[PDB]
Amino acid sequence: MISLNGYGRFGLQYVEDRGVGLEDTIISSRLRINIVGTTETDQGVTFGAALAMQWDDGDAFAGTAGNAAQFWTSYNGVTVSVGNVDTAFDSVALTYDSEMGYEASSFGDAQSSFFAYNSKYDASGALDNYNGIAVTYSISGVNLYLSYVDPDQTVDSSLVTEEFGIAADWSNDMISLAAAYTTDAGGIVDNDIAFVGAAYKFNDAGTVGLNWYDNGLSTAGDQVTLYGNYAFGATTVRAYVSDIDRAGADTAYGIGADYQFAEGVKVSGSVQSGFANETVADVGVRFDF
Amino acid sequence: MISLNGYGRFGLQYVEDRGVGLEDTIISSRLRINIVGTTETDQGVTFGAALAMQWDDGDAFAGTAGNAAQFWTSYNGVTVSVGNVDTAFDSVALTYDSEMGYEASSFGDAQSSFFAYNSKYDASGALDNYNGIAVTYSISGVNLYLSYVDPDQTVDSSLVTEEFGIAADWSNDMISLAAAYTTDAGGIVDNDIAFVGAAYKFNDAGTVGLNWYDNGLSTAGDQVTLYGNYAFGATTVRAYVSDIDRAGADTAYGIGADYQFAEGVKVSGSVQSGFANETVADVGVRFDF
Amino acid sequence: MISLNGYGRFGLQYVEDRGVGLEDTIISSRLRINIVGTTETDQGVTFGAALAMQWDDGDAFAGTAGNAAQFWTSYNGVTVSVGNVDTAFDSVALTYDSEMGYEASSFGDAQSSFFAYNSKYDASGALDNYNGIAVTYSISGVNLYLSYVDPDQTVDSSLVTEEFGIAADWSNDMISLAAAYTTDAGGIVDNDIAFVGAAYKFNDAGTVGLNWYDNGLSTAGDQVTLYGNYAFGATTVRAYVSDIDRAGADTAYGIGADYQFAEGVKVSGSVQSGFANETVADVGVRFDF
Ligand SMILES: CCCCCCCCOCCOCCOCCOCCO
Ligand SMILES: CCCCCCCCOCCOCCOCCOCCO
Ligand SMILES: CCCCCCCCOCCOCCOCCOCCO
Ligand SMILES: CCCCCCCCOCCOCCOCCOCCO
Ligand SMILES: CCCCCCCCOCCOCCOCCOCCO
Ligand SMILES: CCCCCCCCOCCOCCOCCOCCO
């Protein structure tokens, strides 16, 4: 069986003083199409393969191609994936929950380098023999994630730095906890990064959380992000503040809102300020199909 | 929801004295696939995104890729589109009605340069930050089209030439009228082009029309195209003559026929002669799927 | 109508002493998606167009694109195809029946160069004006195949070497015969290749066959491949031995097994030894969707 799904988004993206002779406000947009092939068996083992075709404004050649494939096998709550996998640091709950605006961005997300699903081809040639293996297990409320990524599987293993990651998250109705740890993140020796997060659903309508990170070799150093959101009917208000250890950095912060126009259609905007005083704002729509 | 549609065509394309050591007759073919994602809402606002994958004989690398995305939002007869848009000069009725043969070509089409939907990627890098905005409105019988195209939206607007176009068409059962005007067509300063056309359905079976163009900076100068077609059951006969102002040009003319083999299957051919005495002929089939 | 189908495969591929500083065992995988557009008519003539998108581990740029299109028209058992066609030497029955393992490979397959359906784009630019024409006819039990491939159809025909091929196969319940002949195979002057094969289904469960080849200009020379397979319920055992004329070559051989896990899911492995003593092994799964 083959299924197709995806989303489109478009809106205005403002970057204060973007560059000499550059427009500060542009129309930023993205089209993402996922092609998923699945083979179900009467034994209860499902086999699947996925490809993504993603276009973003500014992409080279004004064209769209598929990325590298991901393959998986699922049985009884357990999923093993191979190829272009999702990694543990990128898949754990809570770590991206401060994101806002129609481009789902936040200075409060981790300021470290690590491997993650590659949405597009890479013209440099760096991903040509990249291969990962990931294992996920969802007991019930609990999620366990493991990932191993070899950036160049054809070369002897001792000559290349491989990335190993582990993560887990747990949730009930009001509290959620998550933690992740990755060694040699991004294929960089000694870039060992870690995440610990917690969130409290202080009503059916609002949630407050705190994420803490060890950003490994990044110049940001350790980081803490405090965020919260509150839903008023169809509109959600979101905010966050984040601090990093880097000397002289400003406190980053963001305020935004989402409006659920209809099932699958979300109008969102945000105004944010970064660690170097960058001022960014956006307003747009995402529609799922 | 995602839908796929498209068409294939293949046949023989003859170009008299094509080139030293070149074959005059080749097998010319095209495959076009459209991927359209749409999100309908109970408020009556539809959101959509489209991608095209088009291959033509002779294409570089013997491969096929997607082009740049187009996004739209539709409500009550009004459609706003962003990204890789259809432009007013290219979307107005009547302007391409002299086309014939299985490759839908005519020397009687406008001999000017203007922006239009880009079916494929562009390896030169010229379309990488190209972004347009188009608005269409269909009252009933009346169609209004507006388009604005910025060839490089990231650079300050005063440093780049933007294209602005407007068009309208009107039809009843027997008469149709259309007009279009575009300033700085194709992003070329002072290339201001215009179109005025009219057609008369002088029976349920035949139609005669006249298109007039101001080709802006083109060397062709002003142009007039007289064309007509007549349907005899499943076969349609078409013809046209066209004249341009360029000094010494020949009168161009074409004669062709279409046969409706079945719903979605059309067999067509044509013999045409250009403004420089070029002699071209074709015969092939188009099938829609 | 548009349909999508395909398959994914992944497993372990071992090549003894693959190279200095290279891993002998890698995870080898492939994703193949076929996009087929078809237009059926009430006259009984079907028109179709197909595109393939195929990704393999190690592919340049870690991306996936479509190949060049194939078009066909079918009526009463007869199929005419144009563009990126299947050729007679590659489509005849029996010639690939010694293949084994999850990558469907065999040293017993013909060791000659010939044109065949091109699954992917070609970055060298060699296939840009490649165009073929193929005709197949299936009486009942009998299959006839004809193919003509011009590697560069835009250049005068006398300046380019074209490939011409013919093949036929015949089968009843127990015996099958096949033969193919191709002149100027692969667009190489005087590379004339030939195939004769026969197989005997010596039970409902087992089959033994013999393929003989004239490999044209290849250095392998003539070749003979003896193979057989036997099914025990859901598991099939396969083996082959092959000999070529090249001076000093070793006898190649292979042993493998397939397990039909479920409809559309096959687990397969093999251990093989080549003409130069290469030792290769694999084990993996293919799933169709
Ligand atoms: C095979 C799938 C298609 C992906 C191949 C695209 C190959 C493009 O690059 C060719 C080499 O030249 C380098 C191009 O510049 C960077 C392109 O990508 C970056 C922005 O999206
Ligand atoms: C041309 C530059 C402007 C483009 C930037 C768009 C910026 C728009 O505003 C950002 C969103 O800020 C609003 C959120 O806080 C209030 C939420 O309550 C409002 C409605 O639900
Ligand atoms: C990213 C989508 C795939 C589109 C990228 C193709 C990139 C090809 O070019 C790489 C740069 O080299 C120039 C190629 O020559 C012209 C190709 O296109 C023209 C005919 O269709
Ligand atoms: C090898 C070069 C020949 C390839 C060119 C094909 C040219 C074929 O003819 C063009 C079509 O001309 C015919 C139209 O006018 C008559 C219409 O009535 C006929 C059937 O409905
Ligand atoms: C137009 C469809 C996309 C196919 C175009 C890809 C173009 C890539 O090459 C650009 C020229 O540079 C040469 C690249 O190196 C070889 C790539 O392919 C080989 C392995 O799959
Ligand atoms: C790390 C290198 C190992 C990876 C190579 C996998 C090789 C595995 O074995 C190849 C298949 O050989 C077995 C076939 O013959 C016996 C068949 O009966 C067995 C079950 O149906």
Image: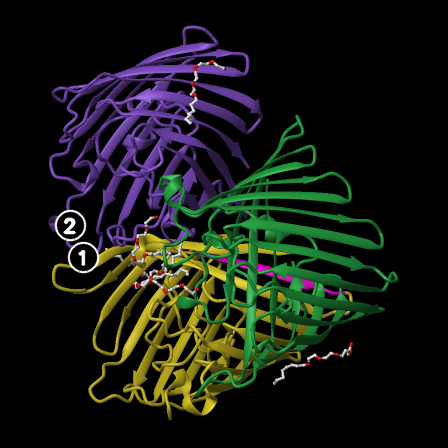
Chain colours: A purple, B green, C yellow
The disc placed on residue A157 is: 2
Looking at the rendered structure, the secondary structure element under dot 1 is loop
Image side of residue B144 versus residue C241, left or right? right
Residue at 20%, 86% in the rendered image: C248
Q: Do the residues labelled 1 and 2 touch (CB within 8 Å)?
A: yes
| Vertical comparison of B247 with B155: above or below | below
- Looking at the rendering, the stretch of residues picked out in magenta corresponds to C32-41
Q: In which quarter of the image is the N terminus of chain B?
A: top right
Q: In which quarter of the image is ligand 5?
A: bottom left
Instruction: Tell which of A251 and B263 is nearer to you.
Output: A251
Q: Position of residue A53 (x, y in %)?
A: 44, 47
* Residue at x 42% of width, y 59% of height: C54
Residue C61 pos. (x, y %): 31, 55
Q: Where is residue B260 in the image (x, y as percent from the top left)?
A: 76, 67
Q: How many labels does the image show?
A: 2
In front: A152, or A6?
A: A6
Question: In this orientation, does residue C265 appear?
Answer: no
Chain of the residue under label 1: C
